[PDB]
Image (cartoon, rainbow over all chains, first blue to last red; front, side, top):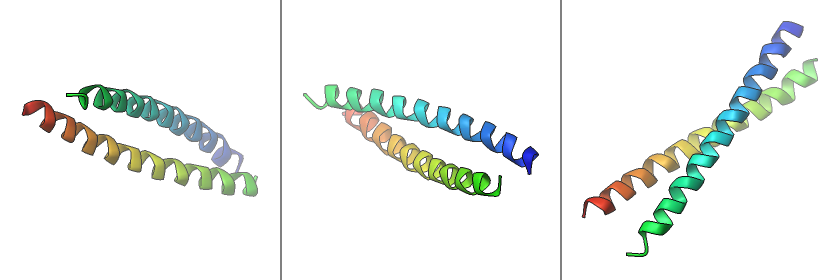
Length: 39
Length: 39
């Protein structure tokens, strides 16, 4: 169970980093869309 | 440790749900942006 826990924490951290990267990409794309929607 | 694994799995599945939702949102928004830019 300790072996389960260690890589479970590792993959949770990796998924959190991926979530942060995806959120940053969403922010960038929504700023781009807001800029383009002017005209 | 069983409780730790339980809420770690809960947070994990929430993470994949958020990742899937944001990925599909990015796909649709990029498709819309490309279609609008094509004009």
